[PDB]
Image: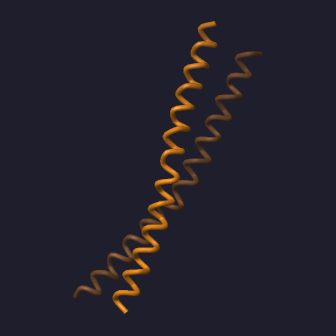
Chain colours: A brown, B orange
Amino acid sequence: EQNQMLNHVNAQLNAINSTLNIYLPKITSMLNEVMKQNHVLSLQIEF
Amino acid sequence: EQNQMLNHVNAQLNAINSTLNIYLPKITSMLNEVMKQNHVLSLQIEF
């Protein structure tokens, strides 16, 4: 019982944790693009 | 077998979880900067 439950812990956590690794660089890039776009809006307002 | 698989679980999860700890303060700082920049845009529109 203990080893198979631990294998279940391994597979569930590794799969969710790899999913988190995939998601976070998307968030960082999107925020950088938002800040750049806000900078473009500032330049348009100065125009 | 069980101990080495548990060591693999420890190393994979600790490495991913430290990576998440590195990523999240960047997201919080970037959001604070975006809100500050939106405030700057509001002041420019009031001008």
Name the spot of residue A18 as percent of width and height, x first. 49, 67
Residue A4 location, x and y as percent? 29, 86
A28 left or right, relative to A18? right
Q: Residue furthest top?
A: B47
Q: Position of residue A10 (x, y in %)?
A: 37, 77
Q: Is residue A41 above or below residue B25?
A: above
* Residue depicted at 63% across the width and 13% down the height: B44
| Residue closer to the observer: B5 or A46 | B5
Task: Report whether B11 appears left or right of B42.
Answer: left
Hey, which quadrant is residue A30 in on the image?
A: top right
In this view, the residue in front, B1 or B39, is B1
> Which of A40/A2 is in front?
A2
* Quarter of the image with the C terminus of chain A in it: top right
Q: Position of residue A6 (x, y in %)?
A: 31, 81
Q: Which residue occupies 57% across, 24% down?
A: B38
As displayed, is residue A46 above or below residue A33?
A: above
Indicate left or right for A12 with A35 as reference. Answer: left
Residue lying furthest right in this view? Answer: A47
Residue plotted at (24% across, 85% down) = A2
